[PDB]
Amino acid sequence: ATFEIVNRCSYTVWAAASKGDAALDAGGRQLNSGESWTINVEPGTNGGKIWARTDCYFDDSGSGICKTGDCGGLLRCKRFGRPPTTLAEFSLNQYGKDYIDISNIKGFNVPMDFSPTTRGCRGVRCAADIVGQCPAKLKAPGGGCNDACTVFQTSEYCCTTGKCGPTEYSRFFKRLCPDAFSYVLDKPTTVTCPGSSNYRVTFCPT
């Protein structure tokens, strides 16, 4: 499957693509404002994520640090990134279907649109100013708006027992971005697309 990753932000981002134990395609790349990066994702990929990283410094060997979304200091991510990270999530060719969603479960750093470029399903978007509106206790100094599980590490926010409800913090993310997951047991906002669809992830779509 092809993913086109487009940076419409006025600032540079470092895109990342991983399935948690391996890079997807090259795993990461710098995207200046306006740049597009096309990656190929193997069919059947389960649990892939794409996210943006902000304020990165990397040396010639691809080693460095980012203020949001850092994946163990590598330009080319093999693992998932440190919150806060707005997440495009996907599982492809699962019994004939693709499933896509945007998640705020690991916080929010950059607004995002996640849309198919082939026919047969709709896209999802979280483009509100969550960082500007972020509650004081969730604000991350590096930038971004953390989720409550990251900040407070309780069974309720992290849903560790498999029973948890919405919270004041999850409802904040949900109020600004209803089409993104706001906590682990949120009513799902997954979209079902035809198997082997292609997609575009746009940072700062508005």
Image: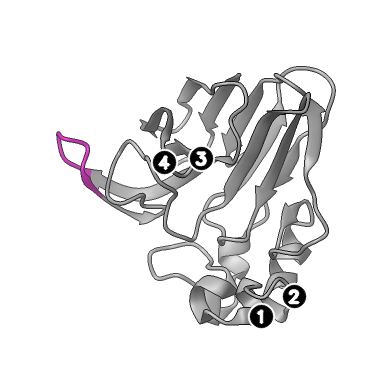
Label 3 near label 4: C-beta < 8 Å?
yes
Circle 2: residue type: Lys
Q: Nearest the camera: 165 or 96?
A: 96
The magenta segment: 58-64
Q: What residue lies at 85% left-to-right and 22% top-to-bottom?
A: 120
Q: Any magenta on residue 62? A: yes
Mark earlier in primary sequence (3, 1): 3
Circle 4: residue type: Val
Pointer 3: what residue? 9
Mark earlier in primary sequence (1, 2): 1
Q: Any magenta on residue 43? A: no
Pointer 1: what residue? 156
Residue at disc 3, secondary structure: loop
Pointer 4: what residue? 13
Q: Which dot, 4 or 1, sits closer to the camera?
A: 1
Circle 1: residue type: Glu
Q: What residue lies at 66% left-to-right and 35% top-to-bottom?
A: 91
For the N terminus, which image quadrant? Answer: top right
Circle 3: residue type: Cys
